[PDB]
Length: 327
DNA sequence: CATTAGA
DNA sequence: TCTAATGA
Ligand SMILES: [Mn+2]
Ligand code: NA
Ligand code: NA
Image (cartoon, rainbow, N blue to C red; front, side):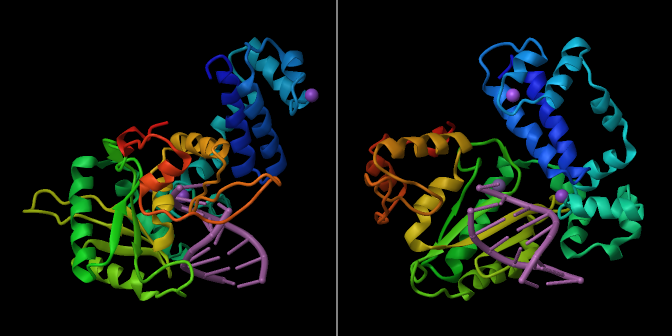
């Protein structure tokens, strides 16, 4: 956690570089198990050899360890940090919708900067076109102060359409958080469950509404159960318009809300833990359900959940407010 | 790990 | 169809 720091640190640095710049998934994959391990290691690593004893730690890596232990640096790390091409891929990749593959291809053609990207909006597809467009607005955090106004509106419309609609805004905001990256609305409805073969309108109606009133300004991807877009709060009485925000909305088979909800509410850790706990408690929890466990190694049979609690009760735990779903 | 765009 | 990119 701190003793292993630089190590894992230079390690993750390294991996990442293989994967993105190079298309070396293996090496990339190597940097990771190793990084993953030295990570767990309970003592201050003193040299290659020592580390070398570890599984995943080969000679290639060990070797880097020493150089790094000797000089608080690495050549390759230094060379790459310098590396144009590579610096370029690291950067492009930030555009929403630009992943490595594209970032390399772009670069190959010679698009290194944001401006290059502009002069070549044509080579860019819709997603990236928007990503390029709200580049600044996307990189910025969402003040809760705004999250509340966002949530406000969303709830109102949803209800306005059909009153049956149930809608919870998840993530860190749900967990008290000061700011958030994008907004995640879970959604469901009574007429939509596990069996009852969809009703795509279910999603559509809503997006229609939000778009109607000018909340959703664009669409990244709208499909039958997952819509990814961009919203923005009505820019009041001039002088101050609001930044373009990422919003995501997902349809849920009503018979799987709470799990789904319990889940997305996190946190990444409180989840694992809870998960790690339901296990002993003879269960199974996944993004959408909770099934009692059985001794032949495994078992199924999805228990019925009516709220966040049921799941608790089941694994018999303390209902813990979202506020405290920290870990 | 599953959902969407695209070519 | 596969292959990418987001998210989780
Ligand atoms: Mn999120
Ligand atoms: Na070894
Ligand atoms: Na990106």
